[PDB]
Image (cartoon, rainbow, N blue to C red; front, top):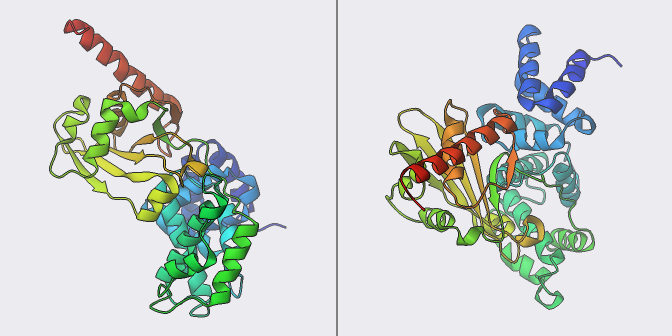
Length: 355
């Protein structure tokens, strides 16, 4: 069955599975030459070529905060037909179409995309607003952790009555129908979600049973809720032109993943950028995200972002545990930049006569 994009699809699968940026570049290139829409075509390939594509990379592209990514995610979700479909079956299906990133802000964008589209395809039937669809989805995901996390004893598990109470008046000032919620509660109880998370996240990851006692980790943790303090008090190696913003965590994301927030570092001179995500385990999060705290450091798109992220990672006494390629950078380039910063620190300490 020849289709106008068949040749492109076969080329893209190869390029994409090697480096997603090279696959996306070819869709951009073909859409330019064939006068087609890059957004629609990308989402179409992600959806139709599910069984052929690296789902980690698909999940990562869809969940990433980017102008292209956001448009592609909206178009991707639109490929699903949720009209007169069972809510939970629709959510299960959506969550299996990619590999979930292990990053709170990415999971959040994917969940919000699902809710909005499900509501739009079943307008005011069982759900009254996109906000109600989103709260129902995050409460269902947390209900899944509650009912199936063994650290939550049988006697402590959330009851259907407790789910009803949490969702009282959240269906655009009204309630969700009793049986509509009972069906979700019972099915989730009987069958947990199939949640396929990535093994490692892009960039640098510091994670160990001793990371919470690292001087840099403690300072980083405090920096999330402090006001007008310089980031150089946390990371000496990054210089004095680095400014910061903090994205505070949504409560449910904290429960779900151990998320504590994201600090965005921007160099005022160079435009170098890096993000720093913090995770601390809790009784709910550990079931899916492990028993260790985590720090994820990712370089942005701009030149010299690699060196800003590497300097931040190298300022920890704890070593980087995991390295993974980003959409823009090769794993080897992140490794070289970090190892080099560690070697420079060692030389400087020795030359200044530090023990």
